[PDB]
Image (tube, coloured by chain):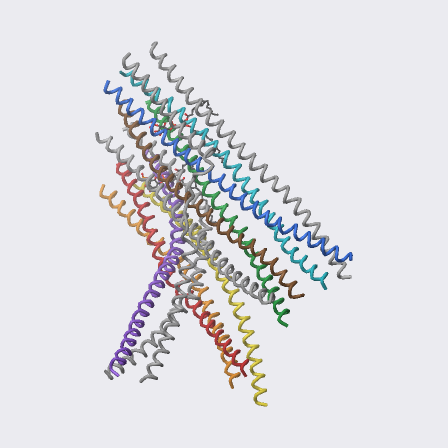
Chain colours: A cyan, C blue, D brown, E green, H purple, I red, J orange, K yellow
Amino acid sequence: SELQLRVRQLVEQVEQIQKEQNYQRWREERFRQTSESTNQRVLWWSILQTLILVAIGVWQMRHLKSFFEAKKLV
Amino acid sequence: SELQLRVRQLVEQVEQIQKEQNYQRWREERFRQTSESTNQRVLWWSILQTLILVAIGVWQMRHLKSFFEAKKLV
Amino acid sequence: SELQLRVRQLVEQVEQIQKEQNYQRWREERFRQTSESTNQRVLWWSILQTLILVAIGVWQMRHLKSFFEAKKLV
Amino acid sequence: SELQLRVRQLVEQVEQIQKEQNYQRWREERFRQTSESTNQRVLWWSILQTLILVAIGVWQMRHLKSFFEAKKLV
Amino acid sequence: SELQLRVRQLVEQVEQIQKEQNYQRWREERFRQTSESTNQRVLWWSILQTLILVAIGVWQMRHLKSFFEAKKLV
Amino acid sequence: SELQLRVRQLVEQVEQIQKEQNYQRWREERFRQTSESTNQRVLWWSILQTLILVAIGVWQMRHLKSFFEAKKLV
Amino acid sequence: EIAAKDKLSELQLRVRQLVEQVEQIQKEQNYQRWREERFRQTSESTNQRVLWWSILQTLILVAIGVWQMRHLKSFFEAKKLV
Amino acid sequence: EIAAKDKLSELQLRVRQLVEQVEQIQKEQNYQRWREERFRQTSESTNQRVLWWSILQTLILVAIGVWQMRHLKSFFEAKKLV
Amino acid sequence: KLSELQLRVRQLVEQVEQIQKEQNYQRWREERFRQTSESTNQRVLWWSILQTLILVAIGVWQMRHLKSF
Amino acid sequence: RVRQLVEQVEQIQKEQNYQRWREERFRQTSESTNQRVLWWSILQTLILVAIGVWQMRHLKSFFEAKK
Amino acid sequence: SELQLRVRQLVEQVEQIQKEQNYQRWREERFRQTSESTNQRVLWWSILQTLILVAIGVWQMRHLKSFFEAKKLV
Amino acid sequence: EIAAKDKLSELQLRVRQLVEQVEQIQKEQNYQRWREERFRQTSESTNQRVLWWSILQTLILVAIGVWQMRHLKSFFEAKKLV
């Protein structure tokens, strides 16, 4: 029944294979949701940076103006 | 007979495992290429934005200097 | 014996599925670590960034304060 | 020899089990990584919330003073 | 026979470890989804709060400008 | 002979699997309890901080009103 | 002495009683704890329920801030009017 | 006789110590239970609070609306005065 | 005989679990009672807080009425 | 005899379960019923509050009457 | 004879035990229902939030109208 | 006498068995503690080349800001003498 034994072993391999298919699916999901997160991520941080830059510019401008006015009064 | 059906089943398992290997190699390629692309992409954008930040910082410095020189000639 | 040959084939197939399963695991783990790291790094940088910008704003105000004092004292 | 065959099967299973032990480690790792993320994340989220309150209060007091002066001087 | 009962014990053990691996895989999928959802939601709230404060600051600046316009007309 | 060695191997594998079952169930309850605790803690902190934001926002609403009344009685 | 030994015997009986008292405590530790896990389930449900509603109300607070601004406007459009 | 019996007494003393020590262990077990109970109590309290704590959360919008309505009413009154 | 005795032992185990079932029930009821009571007091306490907020607004427009006088 | 006794214990266990069924029912009622009172109960609370405001209004009216 | 009768009783005993087990399973189902009863209680809280408040609002409106009448008298 | 003492010893052994049960409970607590301990948040100190550059860059930006400020101050001084 050697052949049969071999067949049994093959079926054991089969179950394991199903499990690995599932694992692959999980990996795919990870890439998917992680790819979505990193896409949102990077972009949003960049946006923030832009905003901050704008803000600094504004700040500078404002204070310059203020000082000018101060000396205009002086 | 039944052993013939089991031989067909094992051939089916071999085919599915070959598909598993193809998808495994391809998906490794996806992770590796995507990870390298993401790292290079974030490096490019973020270093570019750092140089941009310093560039407009110096540009605002120069514009404060120019406005103050204009004030000197009032 | 044809049957025997097929048994051998099956064994080889099993082997292929097995060592590679280990490989897959490694890929995942390794891969995951990398991913994690990347994410973390990004996040860290962002936080360092924003907060730092806030501080910068505060110090701009501080510069006005010393400068303002100079304008008064003079 | 049947017994021996069974034993061989058992060893294959233990190897799988080997990978299963690795999976347990994986679980652990995952969990802890998540924990870390929440920790640092909740930490600087609370920190940023404190900055939210401080920034709002300080700047509202600032325009309090500015609008006070504006209505006084008109 | 002792060999047959060893075989039955081995089969029971392999079934048990297969159920165990199923449980670990499903639990990893579920809790990975939960963890990434929670982390994404919290960081999304953090970036939203940053935008909330930027919007509030600008809108109250517009508010003060509206007072300036009103006083300029009275 | 070798068969009793195989019996010892199977027994130690069963012992290791029982240890893995204990660790798996224990770590499962760590995930469950930790997830519930994290959700409860973030809910607590979030509700506390939103109540803080609204309450102190109203508080300097009242303080702005009080300062305006004080200016009226100048 | 003899009397003391008798007392010791009485004490032994008391320790038997003590042993009985332990077991009960162990029982308390089991099933009760499982029901504590059910209480935790309830808590979890509640958490799920508030992992968004609170945010809506935060947005609500932003709106409140704007309401405050409006009220302030009213207040300052009053002092000028005297 | 004598000395041997003294040794026996020593053994008895050891037993007494075990009874004492054991009792202390039991006390410790009790401590590890009361704390747990407290935690459970807290959880139940929390549930109630959530509904009612939750009620306070749901009192933060409606109330605001009501205030606004009152303001409107005041405005109407002003119109009546003018 | 022996087998039967073992079965009896199993029954005893079931009765221990049976006791546990009773315990579930009682736990539930107890919990419920306590919970309800405390809960009641709490949402009423908060009604009072809300009342204060509303009451203060009433005071704010009594003032308006005074201005109208 | 012994077997009869075993049967009896089994029966007892079943009975315990049924006692618990009743308990469960009670619990359900408690959960709903009392909470419904939190219904009725808070209606009463609202009423109390309302009364308070009415009283306040009356006071205001008195002040109006005293100019 | 008698002994045999006792054996029969024992089998009946076993049947009863089985029934007890069934009952236990049904009680577990009841527990599931109990777990979902909490959600029904939350629905009751939602109803409390959405009808009594409405009533209050209506009430307010009506009595505000009464105040208007009073104002007309005054 | 002797025999009675032997019986007492047996009782003590039973008590010790109860103590062992308590020890098992303690072990469970220890297992809970094992499901913890270890380290905390990981600290960056590797790869230095890229990560280091990033941090460095941030710092540089800050420094640049400061430099600008200094320059501005200098300008102010110049015109203060003007």
Expressed as whole percent of the image width and height from the top left, the position of residue K47 reads 45, 53
Expressed as whole percent of the image width and height from the top left, the position of residue D9 reads 63, 60
Name the one closer to the observer, H38 or A8: A8
Name the one closer to the observer, J53 or E9: E9
User: K27 above or below D48?
Assistant: below
The C terminus of chain C, quarter of image = top left
> Which residue is most to the bottom?
K1
Disc count in the image? 0
- Residue occupying image coordinates x 49% and y 72%: J17
Residue E73 appears left or right of A47? left
User: D16 above or below I8?
Assistant: above
Q: Is residue D40 visible?
A: yes
User: I67 above or below K53?
Assistant: above
Residue E71 appears left or right of K51? left
Expressed as whole percent of the image width and height from the top left, the position of residue C44 reads 44, 37
Expressed as whole percent of the image width and height from the top left, the position of residue D62 reads 31, 30
User: E25 above or below J22?
Assistant: above
- Residue occupying image coordinates x 33% and y 63%: H31
Name the one closer to the observer, J14 or K62: J14
Residue D26 appears left or right of E52? right
- Residue occupying image coordinates x 56% and y 46%: C28
- The quarter of the picture where residue I28 lies is bottom left
Residue A47 appears left or right of E69? right
